[PDB]
Amino acid sequence: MKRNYILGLDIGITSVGYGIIDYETRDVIDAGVRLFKEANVENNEGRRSKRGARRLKRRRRHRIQRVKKLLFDYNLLTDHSELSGINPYEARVKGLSQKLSEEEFSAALLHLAKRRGVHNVNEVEEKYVAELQLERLKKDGEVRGSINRFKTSDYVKEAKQLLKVQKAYHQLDQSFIDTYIDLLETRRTYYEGPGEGSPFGWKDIKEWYEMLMGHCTYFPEELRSVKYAYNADLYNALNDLNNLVITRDENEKLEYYEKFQIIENVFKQKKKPTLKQIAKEILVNEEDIKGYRVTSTGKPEFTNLKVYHDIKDITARKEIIENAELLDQIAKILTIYQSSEDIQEELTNLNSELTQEEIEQISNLKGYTGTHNLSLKAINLILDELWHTNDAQIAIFNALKQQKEIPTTLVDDFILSPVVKRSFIQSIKVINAIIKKYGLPNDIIIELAREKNSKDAQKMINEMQKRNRQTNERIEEIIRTTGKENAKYLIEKIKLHDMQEGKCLYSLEAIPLEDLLNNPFNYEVDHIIPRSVSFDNSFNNKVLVKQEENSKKGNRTPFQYLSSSDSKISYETFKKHILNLAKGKGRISKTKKEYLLEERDINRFSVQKDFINRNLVDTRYATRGLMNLLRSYFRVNNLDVKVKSINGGFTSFLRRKWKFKKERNKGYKHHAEDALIIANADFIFKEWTPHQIKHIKDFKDYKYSHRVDKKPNRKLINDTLYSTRKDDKGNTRIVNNLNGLYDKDNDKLKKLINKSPEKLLMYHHDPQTYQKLKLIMEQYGDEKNPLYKYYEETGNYLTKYSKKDNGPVIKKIKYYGNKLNAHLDITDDYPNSRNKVVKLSLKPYRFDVYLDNGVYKFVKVNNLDVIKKENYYEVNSKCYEEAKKLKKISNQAEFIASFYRNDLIKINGELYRVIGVASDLLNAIEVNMIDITYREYLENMNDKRPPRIFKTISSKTQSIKKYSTDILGNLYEVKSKKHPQIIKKG
RNA sequence: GGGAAAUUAGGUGCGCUUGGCGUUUUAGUACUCUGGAAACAGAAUCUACUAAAACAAGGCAAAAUGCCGUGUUUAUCUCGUCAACUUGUUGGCGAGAU
DNA sequence: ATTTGAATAGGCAAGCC
DNA sequence: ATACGGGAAGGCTTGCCTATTCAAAT
DNA sequence: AAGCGCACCTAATTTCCCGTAT
Ligand SMILES: [Mg+2]
Ligand SMILES: [Mg+2]
Ligand SMILES: [Mg+2]
């Protein structure tokens, strides 16, 4: 309005605090907090992963259907053909010698196409798979599982033989055989991506690459150069030489002729120039030359012309090798195109003086990736200036060279880290809302978190890097000498191999380096702490293990896995080994050791409270980025606003200095009262007055603004499927399963038998096996798991009752669980299912309150109740009227409001924020407190209730009102429309 | 003190391509019961294996290496104006109130 | 004096490598 | 013509069911 | 789990550029 002020900001992961202070007096004007859900990478990773899975399953289904059509066409399959009782492993093994029936033949081909193995980068090009598979079926009693992993080439070898034999007896031609093998072996590449129509797709390779690659600095509407173009490497070569300073008679910097002869005789002759070779061309001692790039080890480093040497080595024709424009084109193609057969065509279309022999050698070159920072346009501009003048690139480009509110799109271009992007978008929206309400600030301040590096630390880091380089160089040498393909995945495995003394950490069995190199697929990089639980992809959370061991461990810690019946070794043995490995100098890091020896119960939710891990301190680039965005904005529009930043640590100092304890468990206000300190900081530092901090500390009128989510088509329901059963009383119940029966510390079954023997299905259905199990529980009652002792003492799993001791092992036990109420019924996907097939956890969209003859009532609208149309979502009318009927809501009932997640609700005069509908049936809604989480409210009190609030909406309820806050946290009793919303455009 | 480029060491993100499982139903075989000299028939749906099918609810498409569906942004209401399709409602923009 | 209904508290489970 | 205040000392997830305790009605 | 493209960030090393305040 008129009064001038300062704007403090405490930007956070979940919050943006703000503080506003009179520029003259330094009295608090206002202060508040804007709270939001942390933007976790898990969320989108989920969405992407599931999109991937959906395509894999779609493509399998479509491949099976393409095969069927081919069998219909060659009249091997009909609508009325019996494929039901035909064991395809028998039919595969039979058909490699004898005639199959049309049905057996169809069974076999369909079985192959369903499951057709891996095809991996590793390969460049005595029994069959079906022979080995039938052998295991007979010996081990089973086929499917982790050991069922074969190469597609192994499957194609079988199919070709099957079709060679069968071609005689069935009428099928080479067209059939060619078609079938294509279906079987074929798949899309990473650079093809989806089919036509995809929002995620692309037309061709160049479109694909153009979309991805970055833009030039000095010429924005131009894509960068590829890293290894001749002019790009020659550019980098000249900058090195221009930086050189020599102590000689004559000019200290190099002259044109000297640079020319150096490039021609050193950089074009020698693959890796050395200071000696440059020193000889000048005819001056090495020590005279100073000002060169240095390797971490200490060697002088000079730019290497990649393409020149690569092509020269193939063919040294001066027509080719002394033509920059061609050497830039070849480079581009080699970077952009991916497969050799694509490169060959693209070179042949280039219309050059290269021969087909030469082209075929060019197409098998490696290491062409990445981009230079400039475009060719920018390089070809300045190349003459670098040739002649000993000038810096910046100097040459320097020589030759609306809005009302801060727009939120401008962050998008440069910040890309999901968490931070969200905090910043909120922060700009918060600043805009203040500038509107209070006019322009004099100063804006932001909490920077700077981390200066100590000298001793730098030295250690340098020493560490020096040590790491040596290991990497050796690994590279091993790959160079073994003749094996240089790969970014091989280096990691080799590093882990050396770290682990060439042993699998889970089995302690040897991983021979030679075997690792020849059969890399037998060994997998495992996460110590599951990726699904943690967010750690660091080397410290990675181990090299056998494929089989990785499959068995699953989403368990080493402790959980090695304590199970599935492990080859005991946890105690493992622990001893790890501790022994830790005794060495640079064997295993402390963090890795801790992960390997993690004994806490670590699941996806339990770990949330635990494991602060690597926090988001990486906001230095961000803080710089933000203030550059803001300063730019004010500068352009001519607004006198002084944007600043202060160090993270500094705030804490003033708190200790002025005796103002950072209050955990007191509420969200801490974020705001941090902001007010930032705003005063300068004044506080000058008067090393109690009165001003009295204002900050005694201030009360804080404001909170929780963000409200109204997005349709979020997760609808939980994935898991459940069978049901009607019990003795005629109550439909979910069927559960007890797994891990033979584990040391598992008392689930022993508890269940003592409490509720009648809950087991085998109590009713296999009484003889039940009585047989009860004798075990009685025998080894004293332990946690009677079955563990049964396995330990006798060495035999519990088998179903049989007269001749030939019943199968028992591995899971089904028992009756909870009663079935709120569910989604998916039973029509299972034709002739006797019982009901269901999913659980109907996830809420909103709830709509109604006032009916003085009685408050509400409807839950499920996400399932909302359906995408052309460009809008629609709440389903039939589902909605049905829902009102179960709630007995009259046609003469007044609609009050709709409550989304975090919407504000005043129930009997008490304000809360909405979480959801605890129970539709009982009419309960879960809420939370506004200024503090209810959990923390109870902790500060030292109360031991459950930390959840539930509110019943009933004839007892007296008033329900909806409230709303602006972004700043100004609170308003809000009005509603006459009817609920049905359409949602976005 | 800010910014830039090169090399090295180490991370993060977005997008794509595959494998093997897991959950559930139906069928077959084994397991248990009954009848039968035997082949086998009926019951039971427990415990195990193999096959086929489904896997966020669903929506397009039409023989195709077919395509989409769990992310992002997102106080509320009224009035003017433009747009959309559902034709009386909701999006964008501007103004006002809570 | 005993039985039934409503409110509050205890608690399990959630797709993967 | 040259240095830019520094050494100092923070998480909640929720949908929903079952079991236990108290007050009102038969 | 296998494996590919592009982008961005941190740290270390060498060189270059620029503005404001003491
Ligand atoms: Mg802070
Ligand atoms: Mg694993
Ligand atoms: Mg904070």
Image (cartoon, coloured by chain):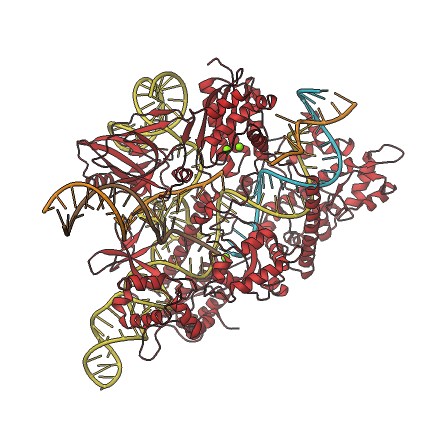
Chain colours: A red, B yellow, C brown, D orange, E cyan
Q: Which residue ends up furthest to the right in the rendered image?
A: A249
Note whether A32 is above or below A41 in the view shown: above
Q: Nearer the viewer, residue A979 or A409?
A: A979
Residue at x-position 53% and y-position 37%: A416
Residue A886 drawn above or below residue A443: below
Q: Is residue A424 left or right of residue A517?
A: left
Name the residue at 39% across, 57% down: A66
Q: Is residue A810 visible from the viewing direction of this image? A: yes
Total labels drawn: 0
Asked if residue A505 shows in the view, the reply is no
List x then y, in percent, for residue A10. Answer: 51, 30
Q: Is residue B43 left or right of residue A320?
A: left
Front-most of A712 and A616? A616
- Determine the residue located farthest toward the top in the rendered image: A2
Question: Residue A817: where, in percent of width, then height?
Answer: 29, 57
Task: From the viewer's side, name the closer residue of A673 and A760.
Answer: A673
| Residue A70 on image: x %, y % | 38, 60
Quadrant containing the C terminus of chain A in the rendered view? top left
Above or below, comparing residue A432 to residue A121 in the picture? above
Image coords of residue A374 (percent x, y): 64, 35
